[PDB]
Length: 149
Length: 149
Length: 149
Length: 149
Image (cartoon, rainbow over all chains, first blue to last red; front, side, top):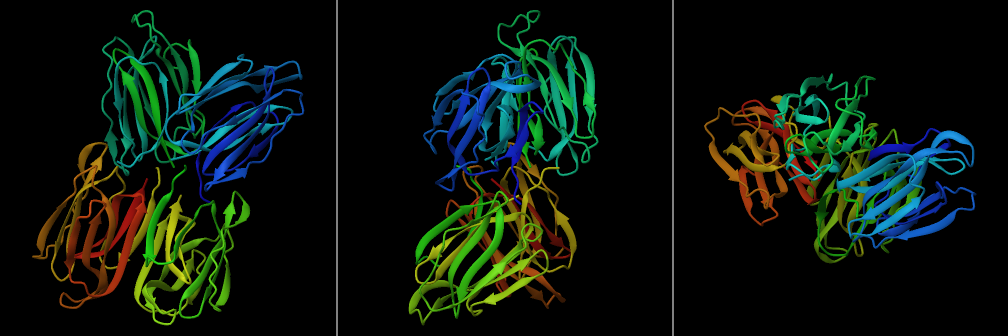
């Protein structure tokens, strides 16, 4: 059962949890958004071959946005974002409001969602995101991370 | 030169940089504080024998606290805080303001320094801290963390 | 490009180099043997799901064997075997002649292939074989290993 | 208490057990040999500064050799040797007779000891020997390896 350093779960206790597992790099991430994040589904590298990760969708009519990254030369060095309660769909428990991804090759996949909430930032000085874990239900309640060197 | 996952720099760019190195675990942490975090040094476990990490001392009149962990049974399962500039020490750049250590047993060495600034929260779910990195000048300008399994 | 520890290449340099990569653990091994080990392919574990690894099949009319470990309570605790040339596949360079596997649950899957040439042995006290490296032309010319915690 | 991949223990169960834990790299290795290996002590690298682990010496009037590696550019990419009982100093238990080291730089530190017995080979494609573990009484009974990335 090898393991991996898992960091956080930023977000809230609501929703059903999911854990995609660990895999060898990331190739594209897909997510929907409007005033908070909804659908989130990643395509990873599984030993050089793309592996479709499990899809965590929010039926909300939010806007879809694909994040293709030039792997293996480019990869994530930072993930930051906001957590806060969301009245429109009626839930007192925190949700991730906005997520912002940044890569080693200087590109920032600009703020997706509303930047309202309590700030979460995860800068990486050495190490690599190798998998995603978190809670979906109606939209993205929480998000955490698997890492490796 | 084995390496170790290094996450974060939280804080700012001033002061001279230091990297304590990666080590087998953490036994004691010693800090000084009064409106922002100043002196920072730790004593780690170097293969079941206390090894004293380099002294990162501030010269300001700050209160002294000692954090003692019941190593091997007790390990940090968290690190949270506030980075914001300090107008009394006169720095335009963000410096680190509060440092609070939640633990695996259940203890929390409550907030040190003022809880005002942009928030930072590294909840560890699987993996251990094993070394510290940072930047100190007059106070503690930024802390960074080494992680391992 | 997530990276793992890689050890070995116990064998010779002919055949075409293969590398199945690193997974979460090993669940079943299938191979064929008469005087040499011919076919070598494994059914790995991908995040609690079985993932059939790439097939490294050889045309020699060898007798095949399937080795079912009871992942995850059961995993490999040693890989040992013999490395030597083969006058019958009429070849001058080293070929992996035999291979015996021992699990942490005591079971040992007997030398397969005949025990001739120089002996290799890798006892593992703490760690996990997480994937396979290697060379297959007509027979398995070399075998190597990926390990992690 | 972080953990590390430990591979091996080649030799017998004679002698009193020993473990040096793990560090950030290896700078120099010391040993006395003669028909067998006797004393084994090493200068470890601890976070940029030389660090000396436990001395493990044979009282035997064996000849002494200091292997001095050019750290961090040069490192061990392979270790191998011979383990077999000894009868002139009358121990019917497998003891380590020979030690040969290869470095990524192409320098091999010649078979020290008598090459009689069962051969062991640990060649390394990716990873770092990061500390030593083993048995010693009047001569080196066994030897194992700790590795990292």
